Structures are given as C-alpha cells and as structure tokens.
Length: 259
Ligand SMILES: NC(=O)C1=CN([C@@H]2O[C@H](COP(=O)(O)OP(=O)(O)OC[C@H]3O[C@@H](n4cnc5c(N)ncnc54)[C@H](O)[C@@H]3O)[C@@H](O)[C@H]2O)C=CC1
Ligand SMILES: NCCC[C@@H](N)C(=O)NCCCC[C@H](N)C(=O)O
Ligand SMILES: [Mg+2]
Ligand code: NA
Image (cartoon, rainbow, N blue to C red; front, side, top):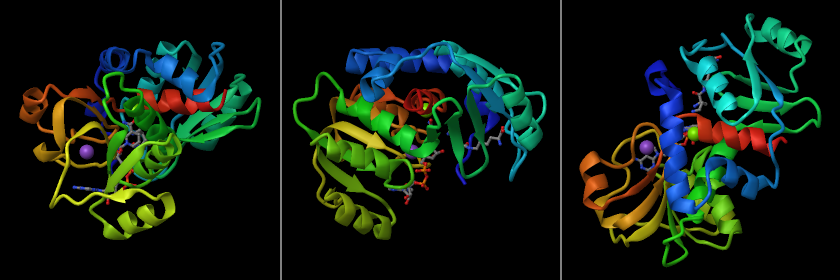
C-alpha cells in the first residue's frame, strides 16, 4: 500500500505553486485551466467538508490539513470536521457541506451532495496527469510512453488512447500489461529495444522506472507517483520538464469532475 506519509505533505502550498508554474510552462494553462478544459466546469467557492478517517492504518498527519490548503488554493470554502468517520460525516452534512471529501486506505472520494456526482481519486489523478502530458506545447509527435498501468495508470492510458495519441505502455506485471494491451489497443513497450519520447506518463510507487534510453532533451515527465521516476542527474542531463505533486492536482481533478 503506497500511501502518503506526513513528510510528503510538508508545505503543500509551496509544492502546489511550483507544480502550478510547471503546468503553466508546459501546457500554457494552469491547473485550474486544465481542469476547466477537461471537464468544462468552474468553481463557485463551494462548501467542501473534509472528514478525517481512522479506518485501516488511520489518520495520516497533514492529510486533512493539506486538503484544506489545496481546496483554499483553488478557491473553495472548505473546512475539516472536529469528529472523524461517521460522526465526522454527520458533522459535515450538518454544517452545510455541499461536497464531502474523505478517504480510507483503498478509496479517496469526492461526493457532490447537490448533483449526486462522485469522483474516485485514482481515475481522476490518472486522467489529469495524462491530460497535462498530452497538452505539452513543444511536442513534435503524438508518441506517449506510459509506465505503470494500475489503478492510476490504466485510466490515464485510456484517456490518452481516446485522445487519439500513439500510446506505448509498460508494466512490471505482465498480466496487467497484456490485459491493458488487449483492452486499450496500446503498443506493448519493450525495454530491450527502446525509443525516445517527448511525452512520458508514469504512475508507479517506485524510483528509477524511466531509463535514459527513453529520454529526449526537454521531455515531459508527468508523474503522480512517489517518489521520483527519474534520478536527479538524469533530470538535469536532459532538462526534463517535471510535473509531480503529492495530492493537490488529483484533488483538483476530483473536485472539478463533480462540479
Ligand atoms: N500524486 C497524487 O496525487 C497521487 C499519487 N498516487 C500514487 O501513484 C502511484 C500509483 O498508484 P496506483 O496506480 O493506485 O498503484 P497500483 O499498484 O494500482 O499501480 C501501480 C502499477 O505500477 C506497476 N509497477 C510497479 N513498479 C514498476 C516498475 N519498476 N516498472 C514498471 N511498472 C511498475 C505495478 O505493477 C502496478 O501495476 C502510487 O505511488 C500512489 O502513491 C496515487 C493517487 C494520487
Ligand atoms: N496520493 C493521494 C492520496 C490518496 C492515496 N494515495 C492515499 O494516500 N490514501 C490514504 C489516505 C488516508 C487518509 C486518512 N484516512 C485520513 O483521514 O487522514
Ligand atoms: Mg496529485
Ligand atoms: Na514512481
């Protein structure tokens, strides 16, 4: 279970600002602009109730506080309930929450009580990070490499295929790889004979998943994964334009997806 740790969420504002500027530099739009382009929707400072959950491994330090800052950053009227779990859910609804935002170890959801729409963090994160990669201004071809085809990677790959991109996929689990290639029609990437990419989407909980033989100078690496798919040196060597942020972007995707 590759879950957030409290230290991933240290000064979430500075992380989200730098990611926002990176998205601006890469796509020409900010995270808000991406969300608008994706869902055709906009914020109206909605009231979102953040409910801490003690289920499974329990409350993660900085989690509900980071969600508060993220929602505030995107101009939402958010609050964290005093009580957790069902008691916290009750408090949220009582205090006039329009969107409930809550997570256990397997599901992080956003539920708009007004319109009945509900978002899952995994597909929402996959779609937005793939969307950002796809909107790279300085891309010469529609070739996109996807590494990691799990709960985040598969929806992201699907989104790229549906946008008529040439999608190359790899996953260390070949069951998931062969199940992805048949269901999506993606070209199975072979690391034995690689090619260079200008657009790369990685959704893996591991480091060093993107080899040097895959990189081209100024390429885009869009990755929600923790830690970093590429080494510090390989990032400098190829001046890789990096889109990586622990919570805010995927949360923005969830919120705008239910508006
Ligand atoms: N930054 C954000 O906003 C968010 C980040 N995440 C992170 O994204 C990552 C992926 O999440 P999920 O897709 O739910 O996990 P998952 O386990 O469903 O998918 C990960 C996939 O990557 C594959 N993989 C692992 N190591 C690999 C390697 N060395 N080479 C190729 N493939 C490899 C696995 O076989 C698996 O299919 C996790 O690290 C998670 O913490 C998740 C949600 C939001
Ligand atoms: N990466 C974006 C966050 C989704 C997921 N990767 C995760 O860490 N889920 C665990 C969250 C558990 C929250 C906890 N129950 C709390 O309320 O603090
Ligand atoms: Mg994110
Ligand atoms: Na990774």
